[PDB]
Image: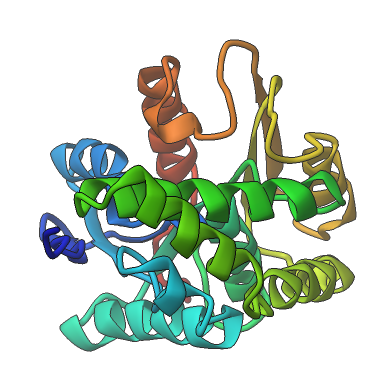
Amino acid sequence: MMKIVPPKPFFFEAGERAVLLLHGFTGNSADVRMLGRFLESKGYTCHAPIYKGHGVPPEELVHTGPDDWWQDVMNGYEFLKNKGYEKIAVAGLSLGGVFSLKLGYTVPIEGIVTMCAPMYIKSEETSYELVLEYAREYKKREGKSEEQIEQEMEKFKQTPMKTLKALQELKADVRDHLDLIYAPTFVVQARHDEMINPDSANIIYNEIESPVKQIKWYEQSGHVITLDQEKDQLHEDIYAFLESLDWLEHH
């Protein structure tokens, strides 16, 4: 057995334009680091928080939920503010996508990128499976026997996972609020998404009130689009998106 080293946030100082980067459920800042590195090379400052309960034992994760994770997201926004960045765009993977939309109708936001954010029901069973997968993998890495993983997996299944329905509640609430969003928005969806109902992206695209909005479909990617094989195209598209936004204080 072995302690597992938890993941850290990152802050890539470059220029006067700022982007908050938000990761997926059970993931961490690694989900968005390559995009961070790319945007930094184009002169964009980048902060990526970690949600509470993430990158730690699965028993610790199910003591957390979106009220906690929302607090890390808001803390990330405030972090860039306090370092002096006035205009902040936001870009999120999946769950990070949902928090980016939520940020859209809560605080001043230059632009939103939502990557494969769920809005329907496939999310509910695959979030459960994802949690089991993280758990087995974390248990393995810490070097536990198969029989001890099987024991601790059965116990994990039979103990409260209320975070899974809190997630569904977040999803519904953000969705019920989509028509409050006016900020320019880029919807990004993987065609062959086995984690969410991908029509979710039509939902987001259609129901926001943003005058400026775009949707792109990615035909060769799975759910985790930032780490899949079309990511370099995604880098470009997100960059072009940010370059098309305002970023200037008007008289």
The one nearer the camera, 223 or 208, is 223
The one nearer the camera, 133 or 192, is 133
The one nearer the camera, 242 or 47, is 47
Q: Where is residue 150 in the image (x, y as percent from the top left)?
A: 48, 52
> Does residue 27 appear in the picture of this structure?
no
Q: Where is residue 90 in the image (x, y as percent from the top left)?
A: 46, 60
Residue 94 higher or lower than 151, as above or below: above
Q: Quadrant of residue 48?
A: bottom left
- Residue drawn at the location 72% of the way across and 65% of the way down: 182
Q: Looking at the image, how many numbered discs can be counted on the residues? A: 0
Which quadrant does the N terminus fall into? Answer: bottom left
- Residue drawn at the location 18% of the way across and 41% of the way down: 37
Q: Position of residue 212 (x, y in %)?
A: 69, 48
- Residue drawn at the location 57% of the way across and 61% of the way down: 154
- The answer to whether residue 212 is left or right of residue 100 is right
- Residue drawn at the location 47% of the way across and 76% of the way down: 251
- The answer to whether residue 12 is left or right of residue 109 is left
Residue 94 higher or lower than 168, as above or below: above
